[PDB]
Length: 123
Length: 64
Ligand SMILES: [Zn+2]
Image (tube, rainbow over all chains, first blue to last red; front, top):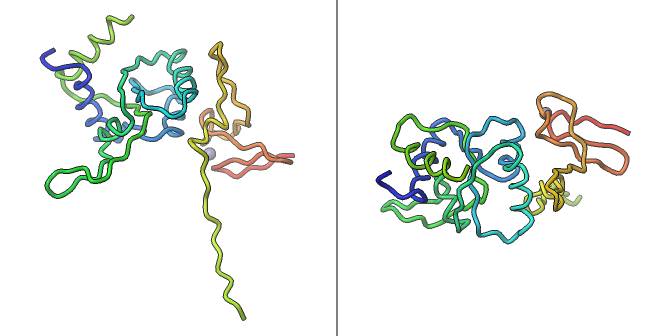
């Protein structure tokens, strides 16, 4: 609860890579929910395709997925690690995907104290 | 005589699940193409209905 909730999706998507629980992509992200084991999913607001959000929210609605609203496509993809970092720490080429799903949470308490508490008040 | 070099490159639509998944305003998820009955591509991976058949992406099955 010490940190902001839109900057609290950092470490859960870091630990989404330690088991490769981040089903990166869109078709793979669509089939991630088709087997019904994903815990959380987020979405980028920057979409050229308006009906794409209607596709993904249809599966996020009836299969009990809670969502976090993030504004930018290319900002969202760096939590996978898809940005090509330089030797001094600059992302000289960033890949952004608008469907980031998770399959396993991290092993801590500093992540689910703010994300899940922000999830309980929208119920 | 002449060197005939060719390779079938792939051409992908803009996130081609929109060709598979259709959702209307009521919110029901309608998939037009065939779902493969095989288990390794079950319930998430779809076939593509062609002009005389369907075709799976994993087990390459055909129909009529
Ligand atoms: Zn298969």
